[PDB]
Structure formats: C-alpha cells, structure tokens
Amino acid sequence: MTLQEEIIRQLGVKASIDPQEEIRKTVDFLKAYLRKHSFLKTYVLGISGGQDSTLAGKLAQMAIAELREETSDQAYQFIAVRLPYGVQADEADAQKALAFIAPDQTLTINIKAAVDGQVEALQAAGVEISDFNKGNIKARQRMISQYAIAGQMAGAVIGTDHAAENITGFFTKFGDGGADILPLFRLNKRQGKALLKVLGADAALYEADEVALGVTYQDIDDYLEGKLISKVAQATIEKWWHKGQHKRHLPITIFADFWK
Amino acid sequence: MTLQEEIIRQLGVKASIDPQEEIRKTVDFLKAYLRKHSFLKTYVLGISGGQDSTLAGKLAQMAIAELREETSDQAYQFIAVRLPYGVQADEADAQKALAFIAPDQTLTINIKAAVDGQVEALQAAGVEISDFNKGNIKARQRMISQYAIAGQMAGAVIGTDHAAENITGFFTKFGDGGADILPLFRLNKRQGKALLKVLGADAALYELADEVALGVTYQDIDDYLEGKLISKVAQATIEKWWHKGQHKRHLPITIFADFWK
Ligand SMILES: [Mg+2]
Ligand SMILES: [Mg+2]
Image (cartoon, rainbow over all chains, first blue to last red; front, top):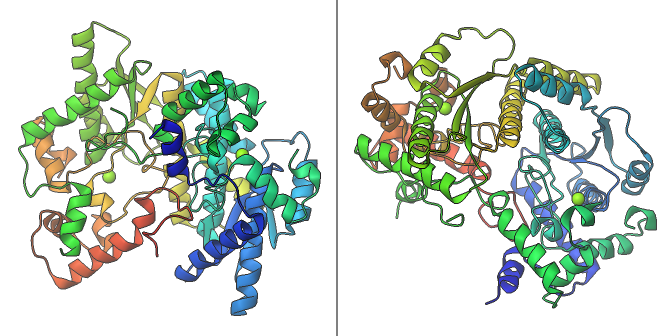
C-alpha cells in the first residue's frame, strides 16, 4: 500500500462522484444527526464568501428546511454568522453567499474587540505576536463566537473541513478545525465546485492558498483521486500530510503511536 | 464485557498505581515527545491552583529540567501561565502551585478584555449569554492565550485532561480540552493525589461544586474507574455522562462516523 492509497482511505475520497447523490447524502446525514439529538434545533456556520462555507451553509440550510417541513417544528433554523475583524475588505463575496443560501437567520459578530484584547494582554506580558499567530487567534475567536451562539441557540457548529484542506493540514487547530460536524469531509476541492454547480451557485462563488502551500489544488485533487502527479508536488503534499497529523488526531496520550 | 470494563479499556485506568513509576513514565513520555519534535523547545501550561494543572505542571517542569541537563540546551523551558479574568478571587492556591512547581518562566495573561469584547459583540447581535456559556468562553479564551504563547515560544500546549474528567466529559470542548499532549490521561482523581503526595506537594494543593454539578462523587467516579462496584444511581449517573460526552472524546463527526448512532 502506497502512502497515497492510505491517505485516500483515511479521507474517504472517491476518484469521481455523482454530485446530486453527494448533495443528498450530506443533507440526509445532517438531518439524521439532528433527529438523533432531540435537544438540538439549530446548525450554526460562519459564512466567509468562500466556496467551502458557501456549500456547507447551503447544504445545512437545506437540511433544516426539509426537516422543518417534515416535522412541522419551526424551532429548526440555520444561523449564518458573519465574523469580520473590523471593517471587512469586500463584503461582496459574503453577500452573494448569503443570497444563494437564503439563511433563516444571519448574525454579525465583530471579533475585533476580542482579538485586540487578547493581543494586548499577550503584548502587555511581553509576548510579541506575529501576523501568522494573530491569524490563528482570529480563527480561534471565530470558533468561540460560533460555539457561544450554538450554546445559546441549541446548536451544533458546522465545520467546513474537506479532503483538500485535511491532507494539507490547511486549517487552524481548534479554530476553523474546531466544529461538531463536517458535512464536506470526503470531498476534494473540485468536487466541492461540482456540488455548487449542481445547486445553481453564481459562478463567482467558486473561481494565495496555493502559493502558501507550494502546491496547486489541481495537484492536491488529482492526488486525492489516485492519479500520478509530479514528484515535487508529491513530496510537498506528503510533507504537509506528516506535518498535520497532530491536527488530524486527538490530543496525544501516553498510549498514542502516530507521532513516534 | 460490561460498559464499565470497556470504559476502563478506552481510558487506560489501572486499579492501582505505583506513583513513583507513574511519575517516571510521564516525565519520559514528555521528554520523548520533545526529542522527537526538534523544533519544539517549550511546554506551556495554564496554572489554576487546582490539582490537575499543579501536577501536570510539575511533571512538565521536571521533563524540561532533565532534558536541559541531558542536552545542555538552555532553550528548553517550562512556561507557566496565569490566566485570571480580571482581579482573581484568591490567587493563593495559584501562588502555592507556582511555588511547588518552581517554573522556569511565568506569564500573566489577563483574559478579561478578550472575553468582554467577545460577549459584547455577541450581546450587541442580540445573543444573550448565560453564566455557563460565558464560562465556556473563558475556558476557550485560555486555550487561545496558551496557543498564542506556544506559537511564539516554539511550544506544545499541555492539557490537564485525566480519566475522572474524561469519563464525565467534565471539560469545555476546544477549551481546556484543547491541547497538544495529555500527561495525566489514564489517571483517576485519587491517583493524581498520590503522585502529588510523592512529589511532596503542600497538602492544600489537593485536599466540591464539581461533584454537585455532576450529581456524583469523585469517590464513586474513581471507584468505577478502578473496576469496583458502586451504587446503581452513581453508576447510571456516570454512564449518562459517558454517553453524553462521547462527542467531546471523538474527532468532529464525519459521514463515516458511527459512535453517535
Ligand atoms: Mg476553506
Ligand atoms: Mg481539572
């Protein structure tokens, strides 16, 4: 068994998908999860204007709407959350995402006072905080904001993690990685695009990451589909895989092996 | 196989321990982890004055000190963190804990401006926040503060989770639950006490609202984790918390997961 095969098995990626089926599978998964947890009424999701949160958000809103029609229980709601740090660069992709989703409720929680208070408290203790580090603070503050809403509104927090991020460990641990349920887990990036095409999403919702990673989504996706890619791209992917193992396992106990 | 045996297997709890041995096992575990991750130099831990953080903190400091003696590498440090929300009620248990640990470095990060800013932003959006909820916000903000320190000081974050909390799910998910490495995992509550006895800890550091909150005593939790028979009411209570806390004890739920069904 190659490393590639073993990664493909862990992440559950199919070489190709039926989009419509995958839509249905996800919606039913999201409904089943709610039906089993009878005290839960809401799904909560940060909406960034990016492909992942747009798709997940849409799938969640559909699950709620159907479940509400099925049960006649109006307390079922999807809560979209906007989480800008200060005055957000372009709210335009977000606006389109929200329009497409048509969410039951939208809340805007500005994380800037919280993030700034955190950084000030660090700095006052003599801890300088880099841009990267601040970035992780923001992602983790968004986790807090979403869990706070969920604690008040009988909610489960939706995570946007999917196979193309997971293989690369391209998320903040206990940040955007911090969530209850992962509707998009098993899908690679292009597979996400396909689902959005089938849902009729504005083409602008799915057209730096790759430069940060040193590898393209084309390559990541192809690797996840069991295809052969260049050696340099393979080594890059495999670097990220090994590096991100701790993000992909539970906290390390004395009985753990994977890190040894 | 009873549920109890299966819980005991998952959490790795021994009916009894040799404290000195368990001490050594933990320290060596903490050293090995650092040796393997050559870019890491520090362990980082919130110090609350409670038994769990006191013990974990001490075990981590001993790992660092030894490893520093072994390697002659001075960059190895234990970073204790104080994480009060405002002017803390009694910093006294904390003081004793820090005195016992004798940490290389101690940082005080007041979380109040961050927590307050977070609740303000929530409240301004019309989300009322109960005391419980705020409590979880604080535990998560501590997670943030510790990960920020670790990102700056080439650190791993120590978690204080242990078997008596784990079985009950008695932690905030992605809060105090949020950590890199769990030195105390496998130990029940009284086993923690024993290690601290052997380390010479002031008896005040380990001798509850917790038990009232849970509806069950640590005596009972511990005994259940040691494979002993307890009352039916305590058993049913423990087993309630077990099933309820399963989501805190697994990875985020994917479409392939089973444990919740
Ligand atoms: Mg994304
Ligand atoms: Mg504790």
